[PDB]
Amino acid sequence: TIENAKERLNIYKQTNNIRDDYKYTPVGPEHARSFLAELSIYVPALNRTVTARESGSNKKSASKSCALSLVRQLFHLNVIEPFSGTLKKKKDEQLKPYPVKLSPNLINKIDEVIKGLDLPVVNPESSVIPWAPPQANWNTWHACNIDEGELATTSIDDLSMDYERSLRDRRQNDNEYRQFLEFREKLPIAAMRSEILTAINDNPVVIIRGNTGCGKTTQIAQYILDDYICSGQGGYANIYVTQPRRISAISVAERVARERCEQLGDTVGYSVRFESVFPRPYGAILFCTVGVLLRKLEAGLRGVSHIIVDEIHERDVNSDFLLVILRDMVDTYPDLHVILMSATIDTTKFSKYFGICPVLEVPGRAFPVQQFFLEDIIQMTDFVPSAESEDKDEAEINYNKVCEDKYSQKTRNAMAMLSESDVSFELLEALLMHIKSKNIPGAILVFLPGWNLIFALMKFLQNTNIFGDTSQYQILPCHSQIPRDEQRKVFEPVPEGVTKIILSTNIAETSITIDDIVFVIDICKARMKLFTSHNNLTSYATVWASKTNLEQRKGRAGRVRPGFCFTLCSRARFQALEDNLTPEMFRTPLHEMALTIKLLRLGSIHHFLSKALEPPPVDAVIEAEVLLREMRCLDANDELTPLGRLLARLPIEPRLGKMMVLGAVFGCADLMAIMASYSSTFSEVFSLDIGQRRLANHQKALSGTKCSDHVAMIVASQMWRREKQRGEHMEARFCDWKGLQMSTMNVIWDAKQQLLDLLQQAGFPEECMISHEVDERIDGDDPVLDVSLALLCLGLYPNICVHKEKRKVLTTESKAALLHKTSVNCSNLAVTFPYPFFVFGEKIRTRAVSCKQLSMVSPLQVILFGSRKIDLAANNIVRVDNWLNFDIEPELAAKIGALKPALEDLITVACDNPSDILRLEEPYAQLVKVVKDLCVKSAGDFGLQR
RNA sequence: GUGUAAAAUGUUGCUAGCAUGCUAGUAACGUUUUACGCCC
Ligand SMILES: Nc1ncnc2c1ncn2[C@@H]1O[C@H](COP(=O)(O)OP(=O)(O)O)[C@@H](O)[C@H]1O
């Protein structure tokens, strides 16, 4: 090669005060002319001159031949480095840390602390939950007897009579209830009401199979309660439904409440995560997520009649756990009746789990449709051409170009034009001419995997305003990012002539459905938001959608029109991929489920997973078991610690509960609730504007001298509190002027309140939960905030990172990374932060480019909060997770890291005796004091500022 | 949803000699360039 072994040589020649290059010297007459280049390199060290003198056709070829030869012999000199470039990287080592730089007073304090605690270091069976039928003077959701009011002296039969007469009066007067009820009767589920209501009483486990859009979600529970109350015993019945999506649960609660024509919370209520509107104790309806039911499971289902668990072919792990537990529930308890619910799937396997349990059928009216593939679209509008980690193995095969040319002009279209990867005017014009010729006014729906490409298609339609003309081509997006106003507007149709273009994702595959849908466009692409435990990676990838989802989309439309299915897939792919989707419970950490089951004293996890729908691979249970045991939360002989009992009630992963323990130990509990709530709830920092690549003046100013997003959101919540002390009307305007996002931080506040309340019931006294307001504008040192930063460092582990330059940062295990756009440390110029160490919250995007929730960390962590186990190395080098280096003599690192037993003993004492957390044992008290002292932000700089 | 002084395959038109051909002088171009604000 000629573009190598010469660039640094030219630089070396420049250092030799030589500006010479390949000088072209013509040789021969105009018929025997040849071009000769000259370039000589002298090496004084070796005194072996090298030169390039080779004839060449063209002036470049004079240099082209000479330079190639010049590389050849000068490389034979064995003096130059090959490729002569700035290529290759080394993950630059500890160019400079702030190694220790503490006063000897701190050294003496640490020595007397470790000698004050004497911690040596080297210096070189299957039970079940209780259940009862409805019982008087007892509430089934609050797990207690009210013993007051009216029920203490009133029988449940009187409650049933009251509910029955209320229903009778409603039938007498409530006319909008009448219209809602023929709306429910004309709904297809109502056809087999009598047989389903008889079978549910006749059968313990009932599986209902009714196609998507049948609307049984809003009606099965209502029918059950009506049947129970028309018999005069509705009061002697509490009905229960869960559902795997919080917003869907809220929507169905609203739908049943409006159909009930009654205020929410009287008979129907919803308990989504971090919220509760619990209804009346008897003859009531509750909706919830699976996690909420798992939390309520501790007391038992005593007093509830039936459970009507929603979607199962979602195949989520929590629903699988719920169903596995509920099978044993009904095996032990015969009176309980269970309703399994699905839309379109082979319920034979689900019945097989329940000993071939009876499965009931709800036939659904549908119109068969024709389907289009590469052949039809190549026939009328062409379909062939292309656009005119880092590596693995195996063999990806692309079937887009693989199609027999017995159809229309494959190669001719290839040579001429189209756009495939990004849908363009071809498909939209095909559907437009379809509308204008077939005269079929219907909604146009397109399903796209990722919100980033959602915005890309929005911008591609907007800039192409000729066919993105909103005034005549209505464009209607649909996702969780956009507010509920747009979702409400989507369900509101607009007059035909102004075509309705709707873009959404797997959220529109279920839950929501428009009666005007005719045009279905599919790309079989969906979000692949998964996690990898072996290296702590979250990938928001996109893989071919499950076939079952493909026929679900195929049957999505066709309300009154027969329906027209436009499939963007090839034959081989359409007949190749599997019908269902891979079980998400196969690739998901089981530590949370393992802790949950181990609190319910349900015996060995291995036996449980053996008696499950799908046995998880043994590596999953092994990794969950080791992640619990080596986290010092489950005893080596499989005995549950009170710490795990605390964790289970916490609706957060143990990586935050373990240290919600410690936050109250250090008197920073409110800030810890804030950080845990915001870290667990993956959301934004502000109401970012559209088309924005950085943060505004105040969006960066709220970071302040600390320059942390965490402290920025903390202070933002602080001003929001001091402004909600005033009215909300101007508060909303002020927060918008601050760019605040309302709902996200409101949820953060509610979660902080719930966490502090739960820590109250844990036994921890209130004084350690007090306000700890911190102002970002001061660059000095406040103990509370640096303690907070240290706990952030220990918490998000192992999400630490090293900043290199600009956005380029280095993360664990030899991977480059950049900063998130929303992160407050984003900019265009080079700004050197006070400390060259950061920690991130989440790693969005597949190729580990964007790190989320960045906050700089004190250099004193190293081993303080840098690993689960002590890391000791040799030759005066400190090993931090085998990817970070510090230069400390072994003894100081040894003593700063030997407090891992100290901290775990502190946590053990705190969970053992929550009542005296403020008044700790005196050696432990001075441990707390000294660790508060050492973790100051500006601590590792004594003796030498820079 | 990056491009530049650098790498070679190679097309044209077109200027002079060597006896309709051959040789040098290229607007331009993927694919391989040191690097620079670049994370979508
Ligand atoms: N605003 C609304 N008005 C009337 N019906 C609605 C409304 N929103 C949702 N629905 C009905 O609620 C039903 C949801 O139940 P479905 O999705 O079939 O069960 P699952 O939630 O288990 O998938 C839909 O079929 C739809 O007809």
Image (cartoon, grey):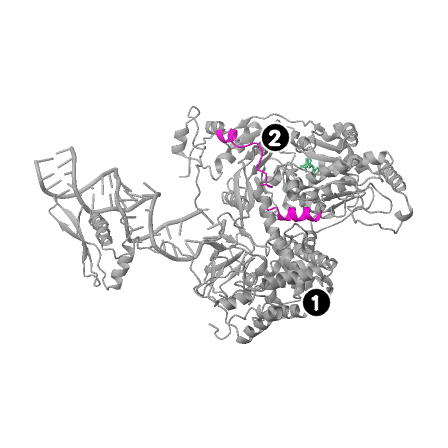
Q: How many marks?
A: 2
Nearer to us in this view, A130 or A266? A130
Residue at point 47%, 39% (across, down): A421
Nearer to us in this view, A403 or A535? A535
Regarding residue A179, the answer to whether it shows in the image is: no
Q: Quadrant of ligand 1?
A: top right
Locate residue A431, reporting x and y percent: 53, 33
Residue at point 61%, 46% (across, down): A590
Residue at point 58%, 60% (across, down): A794
Label 2 crowd (10 A; few <14 / some 14-19 / many >=20): many
Looking at numbered disc 2 in the image, what kind of residue is underneath it?
Answer: Gly
Quadrant for residue A232, please give it: top right
Q: Is residue A294 magenta?
A: no
Locate residue A580, reporting x and y percent: 58, 33
For residue A266, side relative to residue A657 (left or right): right
Q: Which residue is mark 1?
A: A918
- Going from N to C along the chain, the mark reached first, 1 or 2, is 2
Mark in front: 1 vs 2: 1
Q: Which residues are magenta?
A: A572-600
- Distance between the Cα atoms at labels 1 and 2? 62 Å
Nearer to us in this view, A476 or A935? A935
Q: Is residue A40 above or below residue A944?
A: above
Q: Is residue A374 above or below residue A328?
A: above
Looking at numbered disc 1 in the image, what kind of residue is underneath it?
Answer: Leu
Locate residue A639, reporting x and y percent: 67, 51
Label 1 crowd (10 A; few <14 / some 14-19 / many >=20): some
